Amino acid sequence: AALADVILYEDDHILVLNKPSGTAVHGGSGLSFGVIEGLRALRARFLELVHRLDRDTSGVLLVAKKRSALRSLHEQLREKGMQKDYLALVRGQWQSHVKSVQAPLLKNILQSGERIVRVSQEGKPSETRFKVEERYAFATLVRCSPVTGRTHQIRVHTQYAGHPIAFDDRYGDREFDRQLTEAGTGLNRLFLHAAALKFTHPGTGEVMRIEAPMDEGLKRCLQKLRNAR
């Protein structure tokens, strides 16, 4: 209920999914599959992920169905001619003057294929923009716009700022997650959601904006905290 809602947009050029939290976008290092292999298994044709969301993130996921479309979309990403807005629920009260984090990032890949990313002044130049959406008693909903698209960039930028994401197992704060559980939110996954993607359609050249609803769990969490105080 409903499988049809996974599909946000499709034509001959692109396919745009509302990726569920918990589902990997492709297979891991060993015996595993994700969204992209699942989709190829329904078809010889061209299909390629334009970008990635991590396993626990949900929301807007763009897949190219033509080489010309990947060509165009790669180039938009490179030239920062995409806007991806995410919503994150973060610890404490995000400060209004903190409009960006510019902390450079290093990644290592672990024996499992999983990634751990860290701020290092010797890492890859990275930038996220932030805009407070809603404030709760001990948390904030922030719109997080990665300019660069590094691995776990938002998760590490928010942590680095002093405001890690709710239920982030790698970079989060278990006491913040405890507090969310006692407030009765029911939250049971990383609160990070790719809410909107803006880009140019590679076939018609029109500017498009595609938005993903948050799942019921996220929504109930937020409802619980709005009316909590």
Image: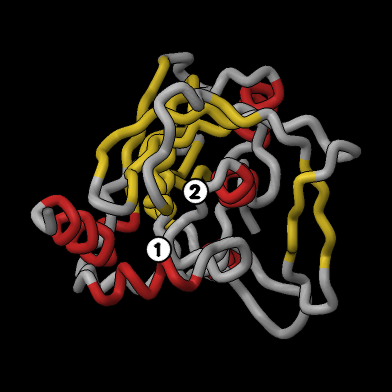
Q: Is residue 47 visible?
A: no
Which residue is at 63% across, 20% downward? 80
Residue 56, x across and y down, in percent: 50, 65
For numbered disc 1, what is the local secondary structure?
A: loop
Of the residues under marks 1 and 2, which one precedes in the sequence? Answer: 1
Q: Which amino acid does label 1 sit on?
A: Pro
Q: In the depicted view, which residue is nearer to us: 71 or 29?
A: 29
Q: Which residue is drawn at 13% across and 58% down?
A: 228
Q: Distance between the residues labelled 1 and 2?
A: 24 Å
- Asked whether residue 174 appears in the rendered view, the answer is yes
Q: Residues within 10 Å of mark 2 (few under 14, many from 20)?
A: many
Which quadrant: the N terminus?
A: bottom left
Return the residue at label 2.
163
Amino acid at dot 2:
His
Name the side, left or right, on which 155 lies relative to 167.
Answer: right
Q: Residue furthest right?
A: 122
Q: Which residue is drawn at 54% across and 63% down?
A: 172
Note whether 9 is above or below 198 in the view shown.
Answer: below
Judge from the rendering whether residue 92 lies leftward or rightward of residue 61; answer left or right.
left
Rate crowding at label 1 as few (under 14), some (14 to 19) or many (20 or more) other CA atoms within 10 Å: some
Q: Residue 140, position in %: x, y?
A: 33, 45
Q: Does residue 111 sit above or below 7 in this rendering?
A: below
